[PDB]
Length: 42
Image 1: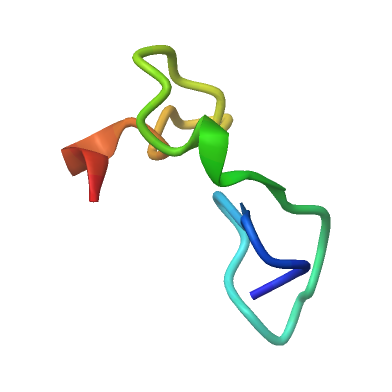
Image 2: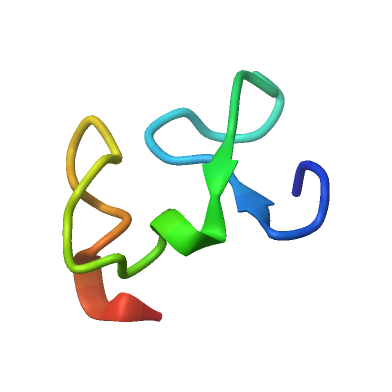
């Protein structure tokens, strides 16, 4: 919950932080600083 097509990785809400594209949600390459963008691909 950022702009559309952008999600947040390894920091929960109430600490809004800096998101990444949902292109970088199952890219075939991790980036989540845990790679939890890859995890389960949905």
